[PDB]
Image (tube, rainbow, N blue to C red; front, side):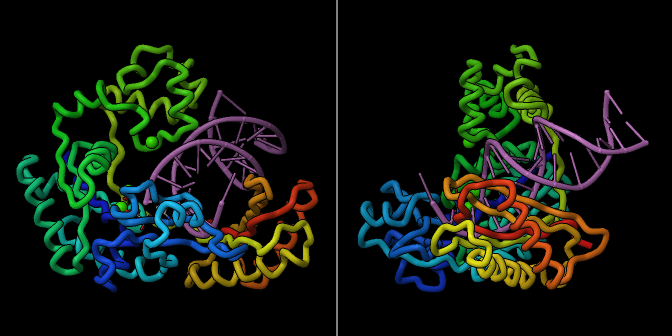
Length: 341
DNA sequence: GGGGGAAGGACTC
DNA sequence: ATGAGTCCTTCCCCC
Ligand SMILES: [Ca+2]
Ligand SMILES: [Ca+2]
Ligand SMILES: [Ca+2]
């Protein structure tokens, strides 16, 4: 198999640049403002000028401003980047019927039956980068390898504006050399557990009693890493269909008071149903982030689809149930809908 | 034993 | 210390 993975460069910001070029070159920080106070919230994404100084996704906005007090700070415009994303995704479909849209800015393209070798693949990557640049003026990174995972690690290596190919021989190099912490799906919690077993590379998983491995990280993750390590990893490109839709907001102040949470919960439903857009959910979860940033939830599945009104009532029962079964305060409250008709 | 729903976890963009 | 969405584990009823 030959897989060509596409990953739009610092997407949200790059899109902000494209609508407003005068931003080119200046550090740009796109933010999600929470409402609690002046500048409360987090960084969603920053361009590379911004990134160069430690301003990256996930940190408080207030932090970023100490580091970069004269960078351009913009609020997230999800709906905009999404529309832009769609047109690009449409471009990529010109190059393969086998295409997995993994997220708003990630696509795996199975180009096995479209190129005869990697030389031809790299060329197609060049040709794709151009198509997008021509049509939308959005640069991207192309990663090419034998399975999805390495295709992405390729891109992780070549970004931004890059194109890299990890051949069958580099794969084995990486299976021995690459820090296992840089393996897609390995976060700190797991990375630690791995270090804790001496496991610092992919190869190491082949010389450790499976159960010792299973024991720590669990079956799926153990199998996943081992299969990667044995060069036997195959997950195929699949058209992806959303499995859930939801919305969680932050309350202006923390509470356990049912009627104070009520309105935040209701706006969340209103938005969720807007986004459902003619998809009929059978299941609903109310989801609260506790005052100490813990995440609690209560759900319910019906035998039938859920109307906005049933969503309203049931969500109160579910929020109520959350309250009944935890004595902590709520900080964010939201809802999530799944099991579509 | 293990299928299958609920709730928590961990990860990623 | 945002917001969104996914897959997996653990506990449990049940067959
Ligand atoms: Ca990415
Ligand atoms: Ca990206
Ligand atoms: Ca990692």
